[PDB]
Image 1 (cartoon, rainbow, N blue to C red):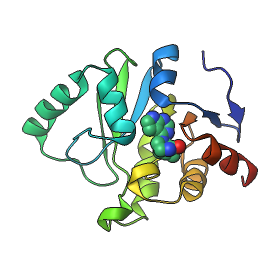
Image 2: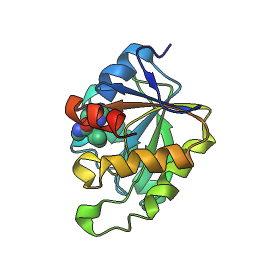
Image 3: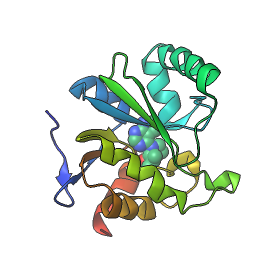
Length: 164
Ligand SMILES: CC(C)[C@@H]1C(=O)NCCN1c1ncnc2[nH]ccc12
């Protein structure tokens, strides 16, 4: 049920789209959130996904952290997708604005391999401060399962395609 995507490789696809609007249209098995280790969904992809769930994602997330403690940078957890998807895979890419090791970006993308198909953003890009061209290259060289990437900014989408 994904439509309008450009094929990059055997298993990676890309579209200029808001991931929240794509999740509402497709209702995929798995939507990836660009999480932080505290699961505090304030802005960027995480803030937008949480707003679309009417804050239910944040309430579930706070219970998960109260039980388990914070995630690791490079780690993930599977929670409910609420009204957007069956599941949300909360994945923590390194935040370069906080001095986190960019080598952890490959570890972050390895979490995608546990799921046959995912709707996802570019990890560590946007407000996380990493180069999106680098994030797309790590994605293509790490993920083996079928990934549908939604890139919100049209100018960035065009650059990602034309430099691929
Ligand atoms: C992570 C970035 C590459 C990307 C981008 O193009 N500009 C910044 C935000 N972002 C998103 N990309 C997809 N869906 C989104 N919904 C909310 C934010 C967002």
